[PDB]
Length: 212
Length: 218
Length: 8
Image 1 (tube, rainbow over the protein chains, first blue to last red):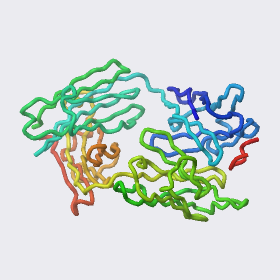
Image 2: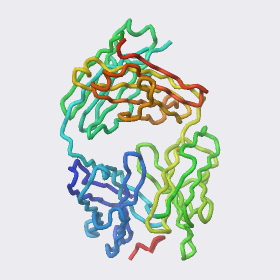
Image 3: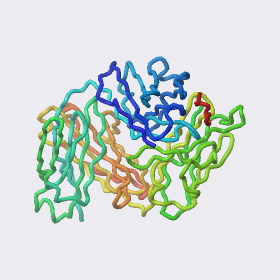
Image 4: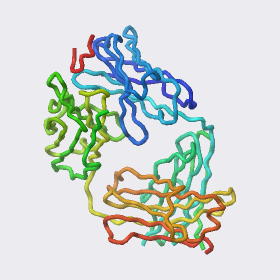
């Protein structure tokens, strides 16, 4: 019972990509199969379905004539060819087999990012409050590709820390990190966010300083 | 295209409790061959969806009998007799009767806890950012429950929606609260010819909104 | 041939 997607990658708008799904643990040529994708908003969209022999193919209107599902039963592999990709095609792509239901078993998925952005370091800005506890922050703005990591005082501050999910601003990512400490901790002691953006070799420390 | 709508959006439960999720179609899912191809899928956090129920009421292999599916025509229900930790995640219904195959938008089964007002903080743009010609005003709405909330921005007393981006955390694995950030990004020009910047948080814990403000010039 | 008759 094993499904392993591959082929996901970063691809430019207008570009093409071929996804693959290697199967094992069952009679491959017996089952119809499907592709389903999950967009960043966590919605699920059925993309394509193919009969066991590859004889019959099915698509929703939105991808008809643009996507092509195929399979190689001799190699126990399912394929999805995608063309004229747009930013909205950024998603996790899952293969599955059908028997009792539409998608009895799913793979772990392969990730597709459609974007023309180039590697770009974040700008890191301190968030000091314009004001028992006190909340500080760090703004990590305009980076690509994902991900970034943020810690506070090199990891000495773990409680009361959370980092909001990145959002797309233009075609760059932005997030903030929040830290809450006792009021007697800051500004009496120093509080610094540690930002890392591996793709761009970025490591930044930003100390938070009280506002007027 | 038939539409699948799920209610509620989110269902807060305590472990031990009974749970009921609803799924409705915009038209009858009863197929001409006498079957109703209504299916339920569970997606646990960080994992792939798994089949739970097919043909309305048939449990898939391995699925424990605390799960049960029912309903007919357009109205369907998934019930859980006693919710366990492993049951937490997003439940999607699915219809296979009509072209094209369609998923419902999902229902999150999440953890119930005591109500908590958000802690609201506002942060003026850093001087360093202004050197780059940009100005992002940030508002945190932290550690609130329940998850529903809305934020309003005011510039010089007037509401502002353009340039606002929001981000929501998933339910916190430690204290089961929720948080949200709101970021209003302006040009240096826009920021420097207005002075009063306000973040307004509305949440069921209070009749009046929580207001946080600063004056740029100060 | 399965629920959706996809088994040829």
